[PDB]
Image: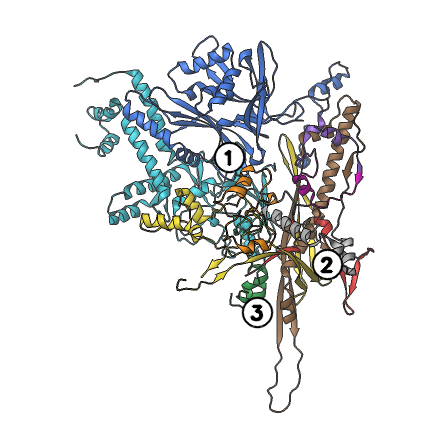
Chain colours: A red, C brown, D orange, E blue, F yellow, G purple, H cyan, I green
Amino acid sequence: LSQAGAHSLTPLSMDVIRLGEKTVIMENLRRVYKNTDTKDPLERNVDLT
Amino acid sequence: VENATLARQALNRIQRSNILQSFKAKMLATLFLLNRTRDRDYVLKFLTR
Amino acid sequence: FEAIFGTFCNRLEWVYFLTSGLAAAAHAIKFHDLNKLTTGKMLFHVQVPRVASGAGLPTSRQTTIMVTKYSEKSPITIPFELSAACLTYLRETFEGTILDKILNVEAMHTVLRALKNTADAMERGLIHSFLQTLLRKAPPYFVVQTL
Amino acid sequence: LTPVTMDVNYFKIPNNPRGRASCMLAVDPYDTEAATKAIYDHREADAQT
Amino acid sequence: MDARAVAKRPRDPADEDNELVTALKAKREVNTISVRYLYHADHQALTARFFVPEGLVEFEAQPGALLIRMETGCDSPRHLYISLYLLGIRASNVSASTRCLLESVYTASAARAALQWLDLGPHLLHRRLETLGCVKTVSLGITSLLTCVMRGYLYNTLKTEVFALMIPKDMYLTWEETRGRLQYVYLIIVYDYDGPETRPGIYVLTSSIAHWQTLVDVARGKFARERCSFVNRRITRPRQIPLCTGVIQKLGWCLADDIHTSFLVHKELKLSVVRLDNFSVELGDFREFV
Amino acid sequence: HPGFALTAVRTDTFEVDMLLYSGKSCTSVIINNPIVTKEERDISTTYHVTQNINTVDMGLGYTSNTCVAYVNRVRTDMGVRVQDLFRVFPMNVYRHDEVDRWIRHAAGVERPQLLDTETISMLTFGSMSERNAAATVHGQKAACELI
Amino acid sequence: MENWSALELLPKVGIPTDFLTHVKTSAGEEMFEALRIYYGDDPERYNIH
Amino acid sequence: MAAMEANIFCTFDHKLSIADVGKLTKLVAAVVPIPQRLHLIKHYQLGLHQFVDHTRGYVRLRGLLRNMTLTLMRRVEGNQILLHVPTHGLLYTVLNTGPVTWEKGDALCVLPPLFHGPLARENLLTLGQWELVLPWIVPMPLALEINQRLLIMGLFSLDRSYEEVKAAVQQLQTITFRDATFTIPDPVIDQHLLIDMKTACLSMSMVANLASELTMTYVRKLALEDSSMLLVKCQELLMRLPARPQHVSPDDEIARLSALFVMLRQLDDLIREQVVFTVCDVSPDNKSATCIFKG
Amino acid sequence: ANKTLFKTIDEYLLRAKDCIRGDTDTQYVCVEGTEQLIENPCRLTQEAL
């Protein structure tokens, strides 16, 4: 599985936050769901009793 | 702008009710802004919004 | 008179799975015999570190731990459709007048737009399916922090 | 003119002085029978209270 | 036969040049007639041409009218071609105001003759009727020409427009709350056995059910009163030998989302109809039930 | 006051935004090229594009975390309105006809009425007996259950 | 009332659209006069006269 | 709107062993029913298993199967199944899943399975307590026998004593057809059989009312001058009781027979089953045949 | 549901959730897939607040 990976790589821009020597990427997927008929699965309902 | 992301066709009953409640609450809260409050962060946030 | 000041078209924001930040969580691989396989598995062999003990305490034995993992399946689909008139004007030209040429180029542009839209929908569907499964496997904050 | 026993808590929040809710944003658009039933039918519970 | 012959995928009907072009190319002779493209060459629908007198053509000028063949009981015209609207006059299901309207529309000698022939004989109505299909053309004249499809979709020469099927609103019938995705449409004639004479009801039913027995069970549930009337006449009035309480004929299939409500205009009078946008005809025979 | 002190239970539904963390190359997705399929009819044609994606999880523990970051509204009214058992058990009647009529009139309950097939469908595949109100201002009704 | 066929046939200038709400919500809630919606492929643009 | 799909892809979300896929491959060209049409469906909706219910009645299962749409299975892949919806009048290859023997030229009907032999054939795709139950494709005489047995049991159940009802159900439920023995499972009497009983009673009443004296007297008159095994076995069923016809009127006879035909059709329909296939070929091992689809 | 901790968490993530119709005035239980499932932590702790 690891040896099947791609050999070429390309640069692209994104936002990053520092979390104690761990660096992670911040992204919102608003653009993919903008005018579609499907609901964003990160917008959810939760209920309490 | 708060409810823009959930409705993806003509509004149903519950979405209309939520919009109405937001209308009433915000209209009551922000009627006379500069007489109501004078703190810096709130005014900057309001203008940004 | 009446005036038309401009006719406008919607320019769609094309998205790709590989250009998203979400793909960082993914290791994307293409497999042309994918429909041929039923299930894929991985095997793990673990032996535990050990530590000597003093008088009176029972000594720990050697133990071997072996586990297995399995894959998942989730296909996605998009239709697109064309009218018989569009196919006729795509193929056929009558008398070669200006209006007939306009209709021909209209049919060609319709099929091009349909293909572009379908490809973009496939990219979005791939992202959506990946996000769904990723959400399915993820437990909440209180569970992981307690662990 | 109101009965002396009218609920005093009714006056402590914004309400319709008529005694029943009549906001049309709650009713489906162009649904005349639903609107009339909402504002007038006293066999149907008032939406606000 | 050889391997290459088997492997060869079939010829495209559209990339082979037609017979007339083949002959002209073979002789290398020109002709004034444009020949490169043959119209209707790829219409899969089956059509027929019918002649009809001027008086009967009303509300059938627009495409989408259901066309019926009626028996006159005579040798001079033998058969006449009438629409469902004309049967609207005789049907008890239609309301009084609509009956008056479309009775004022058909004020012609031919239409009145059709009505007299229909009521004259002793047979039941369905024995006098034969369904042809849906019409999509008109060429007006003292004798008008109608072309009707009897298997297929409704569309013009280039398929640039698909025609619907128009049903008058009083005749439209549904028996399910939420429609199935695929809908079959049927023609129903049901007889009420009152004292003096039988009053026929005429309906066009849209249903998701394709099985005959289940459909007839639902129909018998919906038409219990007419079955009671049938048995009551059988008891009270011997030597009258009625047959059937109703007949059901299948004609067509359409998708539930294609169903819409609309109106028709003729001589600045408005008739209200139900509209089946992408209807395709598939005719059956009259099956009778009790 | 009657001699019991019933307690009520109800659920309120919230509309929330969630935050998900996932680790780099936590899972690998394997895909094939999309396959197209044609269906022909007289008036139009439609093309179906299908791609089957297959995924496998590549961590010996929970590799993704989720949290309920933000909530902004209550979909339900949080009311004190109690649902009628006459709707949830739509076929129980008092054995005495006059007593049944009197009880239903006092409680304000509609007369039961069902066909054979309607009853069968309701029992097997529940129907939505309660119709919507004329207007709603507080949202969905959170019906209280009493014990 | 508008000539939709002329809009479909004539060349257009491409812009990035910025509806605040969902486009179908804007249509269903009647943000605009002179709306038309159709699904799939509608051949009516092909019959010039 | 979205035109109805002719090709349906089915995917199992349960994991499949090599034995399961091997079992699936054998089922190509068989008939599988589905409740709804989509381009891509889940395996739960596939087959007759979804309707198995505590009611257990054979009649209600027969009613449910009548309303499902029939598809043929095209070739299988890994974890995928392709189904095709046949069209009226075209020619198809179909697989004989059940133990019933087919013959050239007869008509086939679809019917819920009834158990046979050791009752150990049920290896079909048991995974996650879902099972691949398929209907039987049977020739017309066997379907007519099954429906006739069910209706006769229903009619006989009325007013007969409980123990003799049990005995009649025991003797009627078993069927020998084309040198094989079958037995109907769960012959429950309920509302579904009750409606058929009501229609049968109505049709028989109307037939008895309509029939002319000539029709009634034909059998009685024939026995006075004919003699055959058919006749003597025929007259044993009847209640034991020169001249000229009291009334001759061909027009009345014609009209009366015309109505009697409609009533006989009404009675016939409740045991008739719709023909789905007509066969003209057979594999000499009876495992497969080529048929014309109709309905 | 009396199972090992990790199996319990897994079934909590997958199965131990309920759905409710989002467009009707009263809470009707929906069928999975037609719309999004709802999370209920009270299902795990077996308590009410």
The magenta-colored residue range is: G14-32
- The residue wearing badge 3 is I5
The chain carrying label 1 is H
Q: Quadrant of residue E136?
A: top right
User: Which mark identifies residue H293?
Assistant: 1
Give me the C-alpha separation between circle 3 and circle 1.
55 Å
Q: Residues within 10 Å of mark 2 (few under 14, many from 20)?
A: many
User: Does residue C121 appear to the left or right of H148 in the view shown?
Assistant: right
Mark 2–mark 3 Cα distance, whole angstroms, equals 29 Å
Name the residue that disc number 2 marks.
Answer: C27
Q: Residues within 10 Å of mark 3 (few under 14, many from 20)?
A: few
Q: Is residue E179 above or below residue C103?
A: below
Quadrant location, the C terminus of chain C: bottom right
Q: Position of residue I9 (x, y in %)?
A: 58, 65
Residue H200, percent from left and from top: 33, 35
Give the percent coordinates (x, y) of residue H95: 50, 43
The image shows residue I45 at horizontal and vertical percentages of 55, 67
